[PDB]
Image (tube, helix red, strand yellow):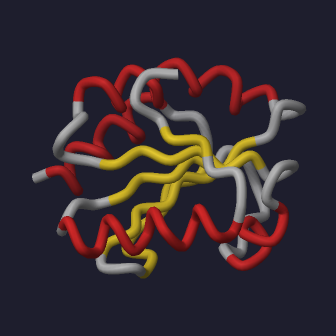
């Protein structure tokens, strides 16, 4: 929901990373699974932040069930995992469902 873009393929993943690089806007990615309890707890906040920071930060969702190859390439082991991408490459990450830490991560990289 919100302004989150659901990634459905490797091709779409690459295209969004390239757009963030061209637009000079950071990307925050939620790597998630519907069997993961904490993922469902923090997803509403991820979507709220995607609305609050729309225009400043790009928000993507990667369901590891839908795009296993992108999750594997990203080195995910625990969920939820949030990654920040700038200029095509990983710049920061945050693991777990802490609401304060997610708010801080977005504020840091939107600045």
Image coordinates of residue 93 in percent, x first then y, are 48, 62
- Residue 3 spot, x, y in % from top left: 40, 30
Can you give x and y, in whole percent of width and height, for residue 82 in the image? Answer: 53, 52
In the picture, measured across the screen, residue 57 lies left or right of residue 102, that is left
**Residue found farthest to the left:** 111
Q: Is residue 106 above or below residue 9?
A: above
- Whether 37 is drawn above or below 6: the answer is above
Across and down, in percent, residue 59 comes to 42, 44
Q: How many marks?
A: 0
Instruction: Write the residue at 31% across / 24% down.
Output: 51
Query: In the visual, does 1 lie left or right of 85?
Result: right
* Relative horizontal placement of residue 60, taking residue 61 as reference (left or right): left
- Measuring 47% from the left and 30% from the top, which residue is drawn there? 46
State the residue at coordinates (51%, 34%).
98
Q: Report the residue at 43% width, 22% height from top.
A: 2
């Amino acid at each position: 929901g919100g302004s989150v873009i659901v990634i459905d393929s490797k091709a779409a993943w690459d295209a969004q990373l390239a757009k963030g690089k061209e637009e000079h806007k950071p990307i925050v990615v939620d790597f998630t699974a519907t069997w993961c309890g904490p993922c469902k707890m923090i997803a509403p906040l991820f979507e709220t932040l995607s609305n609050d920071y729309a225009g400043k930060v790009i928000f993507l969702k990667v369901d590891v069930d839908a795009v296993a190859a992108v999750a594997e390439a990203a080195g995910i082991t625990a969920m939820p995992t949030f990654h920040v991408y700038k200029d095509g490459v990983k710049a920061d990450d945050l693991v777990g469902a802490s609401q304060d830490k997610l708010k801080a991560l977005v504020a840091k990289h939107a600045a």
